[PDB]
Image: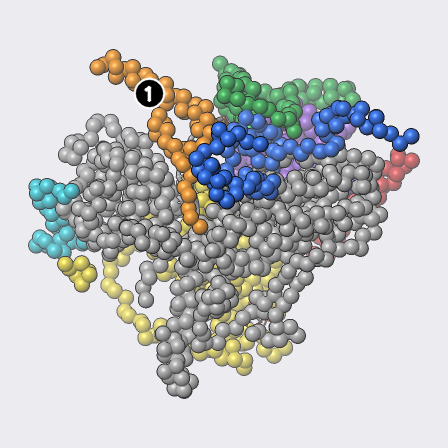
Chain colours: A orange, B green, C purple, F cyan, H blue, I yellow, J red, M brown
Amino acid sequence: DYWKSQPKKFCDYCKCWIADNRPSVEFHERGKNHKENVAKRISEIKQKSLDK
Amino acid sequence: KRELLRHRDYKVDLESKLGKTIVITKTTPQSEMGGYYCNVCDCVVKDSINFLDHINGKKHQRNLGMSMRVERSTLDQVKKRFEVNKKKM
Amino acid sequence: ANRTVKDAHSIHGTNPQYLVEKIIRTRIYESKYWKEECFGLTAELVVDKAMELRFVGGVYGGNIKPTPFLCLTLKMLQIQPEKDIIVEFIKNEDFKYVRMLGALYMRLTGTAIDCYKYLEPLYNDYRKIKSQNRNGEFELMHVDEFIDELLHSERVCDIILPRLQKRYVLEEAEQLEPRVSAL
Amino acid sequence: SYMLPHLHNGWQVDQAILSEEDRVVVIRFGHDWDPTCMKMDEVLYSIAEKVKNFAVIYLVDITEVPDFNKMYELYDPCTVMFFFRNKHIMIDLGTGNNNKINWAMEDKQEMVDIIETVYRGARKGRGLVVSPKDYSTKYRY
Amino acid sequence: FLGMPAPLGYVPGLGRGATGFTTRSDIGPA
Amino acid sequence: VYAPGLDIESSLKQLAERRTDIFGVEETAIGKKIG
Amino acid sequence: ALIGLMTYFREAVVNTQELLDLLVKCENKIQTRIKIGLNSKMPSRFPPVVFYTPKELGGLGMLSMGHVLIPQSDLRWSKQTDVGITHFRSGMSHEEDQ
Amino acid sequence: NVNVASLTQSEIRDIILGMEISAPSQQRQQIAEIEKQTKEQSQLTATQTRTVNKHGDEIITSTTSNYETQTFSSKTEWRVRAISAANLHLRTNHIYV
Amino acid sequence: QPVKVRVSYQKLLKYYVLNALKHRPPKAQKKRYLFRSFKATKFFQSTKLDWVEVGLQVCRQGYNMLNLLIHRKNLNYLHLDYNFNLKPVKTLTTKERKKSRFGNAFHLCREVLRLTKLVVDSHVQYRLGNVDAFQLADGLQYIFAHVGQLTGMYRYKYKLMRQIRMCKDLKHLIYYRFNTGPVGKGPGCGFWAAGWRVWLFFMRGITPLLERWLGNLLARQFRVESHFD
Amino acid sequence: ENDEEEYEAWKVRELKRIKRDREDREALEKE
Amino acid sequence: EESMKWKKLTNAQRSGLNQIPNRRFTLWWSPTINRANVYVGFQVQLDLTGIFMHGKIPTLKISLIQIFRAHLWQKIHESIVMDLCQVFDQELDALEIETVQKETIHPRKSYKMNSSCADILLFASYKWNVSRPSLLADSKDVMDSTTTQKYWIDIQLRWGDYDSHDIERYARAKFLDYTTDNMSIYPSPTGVLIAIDLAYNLHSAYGNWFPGSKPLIQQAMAKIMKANPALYVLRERIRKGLQ
RNA sequence: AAGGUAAGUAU
RNA sequence: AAGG
Ligand SMILES: O=P(O)(O)O[C@H]1[C@@H](OP(=O)(O)O)[C@@H](OP(=O)(O)O)[C@@H](OP(=O)(O)O)[C@@H](OP(=O)(O)O)[C@H]1OP(=O)(O)O
């Protein structure tokens, strides 16, 4: 009767929590939103570096 | 420049790949993944009903340079359609 | 699409498609036949699909599944055909199902005058047809029986037909000639 | 009721929700003059120091700040909502509304336990936590 | 920050990506 | 954790404005501020 | 509490009609407490077997000072044998509710 | 049929003592697979089947979850019969003429 | 006479006595007329119509108002039929059936409109020639004597058990004063005045509550001994 | 064969339609 | 539960830990509380499971989630189907089966109680003689109704409550509903539907039968129920939850 | 009429 | 991915 919580992964780019297994992680990463967030993060990193 | 809606002259092979198994890897793009895919709208749909909804959607017709408006038919062409259909059989 | 065409006018003070119950309309809109062969249909395309009809009926099965006849009826309600188009559907002689579809549309949207002017002359047809029951079973009836149900039964093919002024009431005011049967 | 910090516009509420990354943002939506809100605010004031390690409490006037009335259905005399890392953490209180505490509590330990449960569940990455106590009844005998 | 005024043209709903909820239909201005 | 002193005073002033069953001379409803 | 009361007033309860109504009311109150602890909505009918079964068999070991009927629909059970499945009932010959 | 080099210190102690590291049975091996979540389950295979939705509409769906995907290698399947017919000359040497 | 009609007599007398005791003289007021002020504004016009036509118009307008209320949060999975029965178009999910929740006021208004639809439909059936005048009267009497069966008003306001019980008592009184002598049991009693009065007196008191609820919902905007410390 | 059976069925349907018309007229005649 | 009784815990932690006795009590009597006769209302089907909740019984729902973790329902259905596949493979010549095919199905096929498809497809070398539909226990088969060359087998799992745990009635209703509706599609009209009551360990089968199918499948299903691995996992999980 | 919403990520 |  002991409750074992399934591991959860937090996607920093999308700021969302997903299940920590290969299927869910790969489905999230393959999605359009994750790719858009990754590209936006890269652009923001470049902009911050240039501003600094 | 949105052309009026037209009927699909071709049937959709919803049941073409029944029973088949498709192997998908990380490298495989959306083109060859399992389910239904439309290049016109570049999307993947894993249902027959949802694929029918998609190909009947506004965005899919818009990507075809088309509009959801259906032209109002005329009497002469309806009568000619009757005549040609009667002649065919 | 799914909505009524812009140029269409209201029928019986409501939307033309609203003559069918919202339950049945929702079931038809979600049917495979409607999404596949009824995405875009003009009068020509409706004529093309009408001849492929093999039976007349409403919905069947435990879950509400519409027949192609009901889907075509709802499509013609959606995209309004002119009255002469309905008459040409009725005037058809080779195909019984196209004439029945036209008669059903005339009963649904036509005036009480039209329901007797254009559908009563169809009593001369006695061609055998197949009708699908609500249990999915098929039964044989005739064209005249379907016309009689259209003119006298409140619900035909799982559709509550609009009210008709009774034939004797129409005859008394003498705006419609009394029906003279062939026999 | 008056010793707690107040937020005077919707932008302040958004910033307060956004600012705290490691603490639960407990925000009470209502009016300082409403007796139910007075009870709830007294309860929150009694626990404000205790839960300051993992919770921060703010009060918002829904007439001065009406920017969340339609959004959060703030049409009750008192309402307490929980946010953690810019996410509204729902709680299964057993009242049928899992989004807020729309009544006034009387036990400090009750509210502290609810705050702790929300904090733990939100840290684990959950959008809904189950309250340690059910509120389908008032336990009045 | 407390005391600071709201910037002009700021919507307190979508400014932080907040999502609302509906418990019932008899509550709320349509 | 608690509000500053001037903020406490302002909050109490708002409460007194909106609570005429406790403060003021004339007594309006519990939530009203006109009187 | 109930046996402390009853073993004390063993002979005096029966003539005390106000106590009989109080015992039933309190028993129903605690049964309602258990029921609402189980689910929020009240059951239309809740079997006494879950309450009055001895704790050894998994029940609550409840003691009763009231008139509680057990529906005959709650006295039937079935077990699967090799030849088939056989149905059994308790209190046969169509007796009244136990 | 194991190498002594790969045995760990705890395994060596168990061997020296009477502790028995018994191989799990075929039933026990199946139980462990069912009891535990699939190891690093990879949905590398998509299967399309004819199903119905929650509203009773026949639908063709492509699914990748690795459930109801076990293959039954029957004695009639040609893959098994191919290796069965391999080395068939064994039955040829011994005959009942 | 049977026990039920005697209890009917006693309950009617109880209602009469309670009304007599609880009577208070009307409070003095300035004469303000709602319909006269309707005429003052430009939004209302006056005409003369047959009562059946106005009944159909009011039924349609109430149906439209309820449909506007139902599809307020774009809840497209709830369908209101023309007999004022709220039914789902599909098999609703749990969240769907939770968000499709209406208060007791909405359902009370729906059942009130359902009663009006029943009355207007009976009158229309009389006007269409489908039913006789005696049949129309008997149907109207059955409507008011069986509001608890035809409509579910008591579910959303249990105080209507008073009106329902009063209607049952009046039905017993009129039937046992009516089905006497050569006249036996069965349909055809008519004499629907009593239940009609009862339900109109219910409406004169239920009107302000529904007015307030509808006004709040349709608008653009939606002691010492306890907290003395 | 098939044509004769179809003609018989059509005649039966016509007789039924005549009977239905007579019944419809008699409905107003009696009332 | 014993170890945490003597550890430093907050009030919320201890309050959460006092519910395990209540969870054990609720799941012990679950076939009685979780009834449509007891809790009149709509049913909600538990996700990943064939269990219907007749009311929000979170004390029972939480403990039912543990028992059917790691897709236990799907694994049980798959194991039973596979075992029947081996059973029919071992009897190819005696039963005149030309091939035994395990049909490809939806991953959630065991979950869908609205309709179902065939699980195992049997092909005959020559046309079989098919009996009228009858229960698994029944032995009076005329065995002369019709003939067929394709035979299908349907495996149904259910979690019966106290009132509804007649597995024979369930099998009869499921066979007469799925084979006569417009939702369930089957390769051939003739086939058998096998229903398993996981909450009561009752098994039955209703449908047509070809010569030798019923006598084999009787002890086949008996042995499957006695010694299934996934069924054993379910039994052990229930025992551990019940202590 | 309720106290019977899993929280999601994808399309 | 589709609906107003
Ligand atoms: O309210 P009750 O006195 O029980 O009336 C019911 C019944 O009513 P229901 O349809 O609600 O069951 C009929 O009354 P009406 O519906 O006709 O008003 C019937 O009346 P008749 O047979 O006289 O037409 C008869 O009432 P009565 O006692 O006057 O015969 C009968 O009563 P019982 O149920 O007591 O037989």
Residue K125 left/right relative to A12 = right
Q: Residue at x 70, y 47 (%)?
A: K220
Is disc 1's CB within 8 Å of ligand 1?
no
Q: Nearer the viewer, residue D89 or H79?
A: H79
Coordinates of residue B56 in the picture (x, y in percent):
55, 25
Q: Nearer the viewer, residue H19 or B78?
A: H19
Coordinates of residue B18 in the picture (x, y in percent):
65, 28
Q: Is residue K48 visible?
A: no
Residue D122 left/right relative to K186 = left
Residue H42 left/right relative to C36 = left
Coordinates of residue G83 in the picture (x, y in percent):
72, 57
Q: Residue at x 75, y 55 (%)?
A: K138
Badge 1, how many Cα within 10 Å: few under 14, some, many 20+? Answer: some
Q: Residue at x 33, y 61 (%)?
A: D139
Kind of residue indicated by mark 1: Arg
Residue, disc 1:
A41
**Is residue A21 positioned above or below K130 on the image?**
above
Which quadrant holds residue H23?
top right
